[PDB]
Structures are given as structure tokens and as C-alpha cells.
Length: 115
RNA sequence: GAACUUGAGUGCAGAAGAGGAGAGUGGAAUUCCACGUGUAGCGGUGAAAUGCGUAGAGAUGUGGAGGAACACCAGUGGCGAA
Image (cartoon, rainbow, N blue to C red; front, side):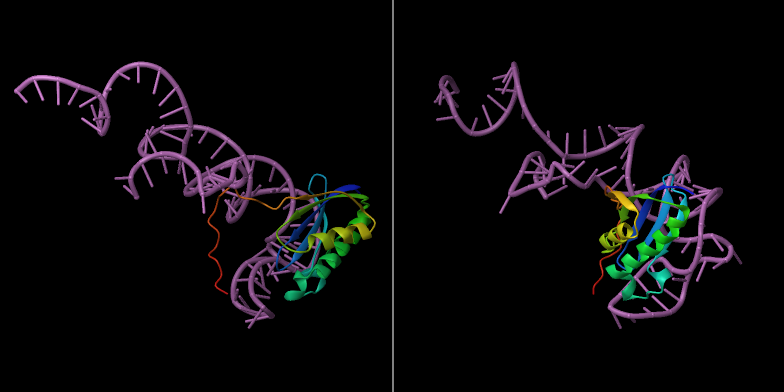
């Protein structure tokens, strides 16, 4: 039973995962578009991000959270939907923080697609 | 052969620079390894599948290993014969 937590939203182009943890990063609960039965294109859509956030939130509310800090990673379109969905579940969102990993010129990226 | 100082160079006084070689050091990120929390998918596509995952993955926290490259600055900006 913990109150304050961080909501890690990993929004990629293919899927949106939402893990909810305590302030010390111990996992309370998590949800992802795939876990909710979305497949392929559907998982990417922002609608699925909403549903993923709601499902993750309702799992956490059992443990008794009230305030969430939000961290967003990846280039997906889910972050806004997932954040608004967390607010709609009742948990107040203190601050959103983009923590997408930025290399300072490190590893060579994979070759560009010729689509 | 003898003069001259503009070319060329030297002296003296300043200026900028990713110019080069050598030796160190630093932060981000990817991967891997160990551990805590935690559960059913993760990944990928135009759509899928191969692949990875209940032998506990992906997500998340701490620490560690190693290799390569140096975000912002950064600019028809600088330096170099290329």
C-alpha cells in the first residue's frame, strides 16, 4: 500500500506500455495495448494508449495511489492519451517529464529503410 | 660589375583556429551480466510471420563490464596543400 508513484509510459510506434511504480521504482502494476488484446496497427493508435493507461491505473488504485509523476519515453503518439487517461482515472498528475534516451553521438543507427 | 626596394624572405609586436602526433580524463546512449519490484506478452509490418518470453521476457530501480562515437554549442563558421 503506497500513495506516491511514477508512471512510466513507453510510447513507441508499434505499442504503448504503461508501467506504474513506487517512487523507488518498484513495479506496482503495468498495462500495454497488446495486453488489452489490440493487434498490429491498433496497438499504435492513441485510443489504445488511453485504454492501456486506464487499465494500468485501475490496477494501481487497489494499492492506493493518489498522486503520479509521469515519465514519457519513445516517439509514439500515445503520451497525451495515456496522460489524460491517468487523470480521468482520478489520480492527479503532478508533472510530466520527457525522458526519451538521447545519445550524445554513440552507437551507429540501423540503416535507413528503403520503403 | 656596381647600386635600389616594391617581389620574396628575416627580425620585432600582436591575433584566431575541429591543423597534426602522443599521453591521459569525462558525460550521455546501445548491448551484455548480477540483483530487487513485477506479469503475460514483447518485437516487428502496408498486412503478417520468422524471432524472443511462464525456464519469468518486455517495462522498472541499483551497481558493474566492455567497445565505438563525441548531443547542446554548431554558424554557405574555422583550420589544412589535398
